[PDB]
Each structure stands twice: as structure tokens, then as C-alpha cells.
Image (cartoon, each protein chain N blue to C red):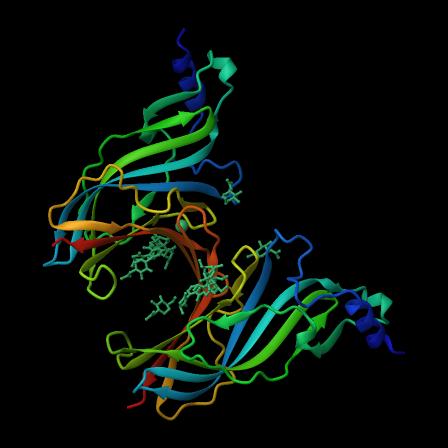
Length: 210
Length: 210
Ligand SMILES: CCN1C[C@]2(COC(=O)c3ccccc3N3C(=O)C[C@H](C)C3=O)CC[C@H](OC)[C@@]34[C@@H]5C[C@H]6[C@H](OC)[C@@H]5[C@](O)(C[C@@H]6OC)[C@@](O)([C@@H](OC)[C@H]23)[C@@H]14
Ligand SMILES: CCN1C[C@]2(COC(=O)c3ccccc3N3C(=O)C[C@H](C)C3=O)CC[C@H](OC)[C@@]34[C@@H]5C[C@H]6[C@H](OC)[C@@H]5[C@](O)(C[C@@H]6OC)[C@@](O)([C@@H](OC)[C@H]23)[C@@H]14
Ligand SMILES: *[C@@H]1O[C@H](CO)[C@@H](O)[C@H](O)[C@H]1NC(C)=O
Ligand SMILES: *[C@@H]1O[C@H](CO)[C@@H](O)[C@H](O)[C@H]1NC(C)=O
Ligand SMILES: *[C@@H]1O[C@H](CO)[C@@H](O)[C@H](O)[C@H]1NC(C)=O
Ligand SMILES: *[C@@H]1O[C@H](CO)[C@@H](O)[C@H](O)[C@H]1NC(C)=O
Ligand code: NA
Ligand code: NA
């Protein structure tokens, strides 16, 4: 039995990873986003830049990658290279650099109901602002703002999977403690009649250790 | 031929101005907002407060105030005191004072298809920020941010009627010229699962006259 092979061949026989996988163009595709903070690599106070190591988990539905489990011997999920499927082009809007790191290879897990889960590591560089005004009163506020590069909110709509950045895999920094990393979702539209532009923003608040 | 009286009695026989006028409470009510800037009453640079005179036009559909024109001898619109109908409780979120004007009497125009139009004057007081960085390089940025006080975005959703503040009725200020008043719509939601909170913001940019 080569059921996974057969399923793969059946699924991608006529599949384009360039196309937002909705049946209807003016229907939206929803993506949830989870940010896991691995490590504060550097809080540069000279240039006010945070370099962080992150994991990004994106979850969405692909209308064209579903199957009947009964036709494939009960097989209900497969893990494949991520570049085989359409992926949301979510990026850090407020990146401080135009520097491009070489893309690590990643995989997606594809479930029989078209549910796709994608974990990817990332090094981010972004500006922070000193804050000595709000509790705990000796801080660096480091916003991380994420969204689609090319799709508006009626094409790809983005949601926070969690109330905050995920700190459960975090390794402590000797100089900075993480006070909080609350997540919000912003949507802006211009004038009467523009398309909506959503983001999710994590406000990483760092407290200077004493 | 007292058709307007007959219509009024028929419309308001069993009507409550306390209830958001949707047939299904889980459905949204859409409101469009137009701001007309009448006058800059005071640009207080000591306290960084703008006092402005505005007209606010709100338009929305009332599901319970529709009628068949052909049943009322073709009557298709009536003008009545505004406190007779449910009204959106849109307010200036970023008001600077406790501390409001005594409310004046206003009217709404009610169209046969349930479309209600409501003009009301307002005196607003709000903080501004000095800006000498961006063109035209000697400015006051005065944001005016409006939204419902008690309803979230799934209950009452607000939209800009125009691309900008309406300046067609504006009387010039001797000290300040209006450089622009672009309008945007912002929506924020907190964490994974909160309701959405929309506003419309007018960024009134004032240029100092030399
Ligand atoms: C295709 C690249 N794309 C990147 C953009 C980038 O958007 C952002 O950076 C951004 C989005 C929401 C909130 C804040 C944002 N932001 C930041 O956080 C930093 C940066 C200054 C900024 O604008 C994504 C959304 C939209 O594309 C769907 C853009 C807008 C759509 C439209 C707008 O034209 C003015 C605008 C674009 O300029 C080009 C487009 O022209 C067809 C775009 O490049 C981005 O503008 C910043 C903006 C477009
Ligand atoms: C009922 C009064 N209402 C006024 C508020 C006030 O909202 C704002 O001032 C506001 C809204 C959007 C964007 C920016 C806003 N804002 C500010 O919050 C400060 C600044 C002046 C400003 O512009 C409207 C939205 C929501 O109510 C539907 C509120 C929130 C809903 C919820 C939130 O608490 C968890 C929050 C409230 O505190 C109370 C509520 O608890 C039942 C509320 O009073 C306002 O918070 C500022 C906020 C609520
Ligand atoms: C996208 O998410 C919103 C909010 O949960 C939901 O109402 C809508 O039906 C979703 N649309 C699709 C196509 O999944
Ligand atoms: C950081 O992001 C939060 C959430 O969007 C926002 O309220 C705050 O103003 C941002 N901080 C700065 C300095 O822009
Ligand atoms: C509210 O407005 C949007 C257009 O922006 C529309 O799609 C939606 O159907 C409207 N809802 C109601 C109840 O009018
Ligand atoms: C004024 O409002 C605009 C539009 O929402 C916003 O981008 C800008 O940051 C605001 N300015 C200040 C000083 O809050
Ligand atoms: Na959110
Ligand atoms: Na708008």
C-alpha cells in the first residue's frame, strides 16, 4: 500500500501554489497567526533595534486540498515541503532592515479537511522606543507588526490565535526581562471606499533588569 | 388629507427609540458619518487644545420605520424631532474636557425605505500635537476620533461618508489655514477573541499663517 503517494499525486495533479485557494475570488481566506518568542538575540540601545528569534505558526484552510479518508486507507494528514502549497505572504511590516536571510526549508501539515498548519522560524529586526513612563517604568517597547504583503483584508484576513505572544519556549535574557507581549489586531481603511488593510501587532514590553 | 399624521401614528404606534433598530440582534447596523468643519473657534497653543465647530451628519437604516408610499398618497419622506427615533450614540472619543455643551434640538429626515439622515451641530474640544517635521512644516495636527459609546463593531459599524472632512461650508481662520482633513477608519480587537471596536478619525492638519 502506497496510499500517501497516491493521495499526494491526486491532490497536486492540478494544483497551483500561486493561487489563493478559494473557490470564489471575492470570498475571503482566513489565517490565524501565532508568534512564539524563542530568544532576544540583541536589544541594541545605540540604534534602538531589537533582533529577535521567533517561530511563526500560520493556520488556514485550503479549499483544494481535502480528501475522503476512506479512499486512502484512513490516512488523515500528511507533512510535505511548505513551498508545494499556496502560503499566506505574511511579513513583518515594520522590519528595520532590507537585509534578506536565506529562507530555511519548512514543512506544512495538511489535514484531510483542508486545514493547513505551517511553522516557520524567523529572525526579526525592528525598532523599539524607550519607555520610562509606564509600569514597570524602565522599559523598551518593541512592536512587531505582521500582515500580508500583497493581499487586502477582503482577500486574506488575519487573526490572532492567542491573546499574546507565546512565551512557553522562551529562554531568558540576562539584561532584559519580558514584562508582557499582548497581541492586538488592527484594520485601517482610507476615506470612503478603500479596501481594508489588517495587521496583527505584538507589543513586546521589555523591562531593564536590576 | 392628513396623510403625514396617519403615517406618523402608524410608524410610532409600537416603536421604541431605546432599541437598535435591527430585526435580528446578531445582525449589524451600518452608519455612515460625515463631518463638516464650520469654524476653528480656538487653536489654543498654550494648552494644545483645538476648539472646533462642526456639523455631524449620520445616515443609517431603521428596519422598523419603513412604509409603502402608495398607502400614504405618495408621501415618501418626513422630518421629525430626532429624539423620536433610535440614534447612534456616536461621540468624540478623544474629547479633552469633562464637560459638554447643553444639547440643542435637532431633526431627522425619515425616508420611506427606512433611511434616516441626522444632522447635528457640535462644539468639540480635543488635543493637538505640534508638527514641524512634515509638509508644510509649521503645523498643528488635530485628530478627531469618533465612534459609538456603547456598541461594538458587530452591533453598530461606522463608515466614512467621504474621503475627508467636508470643508465646503468652512469660514477661514485668520491664524491657521486648513492644509487637509483626511478621514480614515480604524478597527481594533484585543487578543484572540474580543469584539471589534471601530472608529473614524479625521486628521485635521492646520498650517500656521506666516
Ligand atoms: C503590495 C505591497 N503592499 C504592502 C503594504 C504594506 O503595508 C504596511 O506596511 C502596513 C499595513 C498596515 C498597517 C501598517 C503598515 N505599516 C507598517 O507597519 C510600517 C509601514 C510604514 C506601514 O505602512 C501591505 C498592504 C497593501 O498591500 C496589500 C499595501 C498598500 C496597497 C496599495 C497601497 O498603495 C498606496 C499600499 C502599497 O503602497 C501599494 C498598493 O498599491 C496597489 C503597499 O506597497 C503598502 O503601502 C505601505 C501596503 C501595499
Ligand atoms: C461602554 C463605554 N465604552 C467606551 C469605549 C471608548 O472607546 C474609545 O475611547 C476608543 C475606541 C476605539 C479606539 C480608540 C479609543 N480611544 C480610547 O480608548 C482613548 C482615546 C480617547 C481613544 O480614542 C467605546 C468602545 C467600547 O464600548 C463599546 C469601550 C470598551 C468596551 C468594554 C471595554 O472594557 C473592557 C471598554 C470600556 O472600558 C468598557 C467595556 O466594558 C463593558 C469602554 O468604557 C471604553 O474603553 C475605553 C470603550 C467601552
Ligand atoms: C472568516 O472568519 C470570520 C470570523 O470568524 C467568519 O465569520 C467567516 O465566516 C470566515 N470566512 C471563511 C471563508 O472562512
Ligand atoms: C505599538 O502597537 C500598539 C498596538 O498596535 C499601539 O497601540 C502603539 O501605539 C504602538 N507603539 C508605537 C510606539 O507606535
Ligand atoms: C454593512 O455594510 C457592508 C458594506 O461595507 C455590507 O456588506 C453589509 O451587508 C452591511 N450590512 C447591513 C446590515 O446593512
Ligand atoms: C492621528 O490619527 C491618525 C489616523 O488614525 C494616526 O495615524 C495618527 O498617528 C494620529 N496622531 C496622533 C498624534 O495620535
Ligand atoms: Na486581536
Ligand atoms: Na475610512
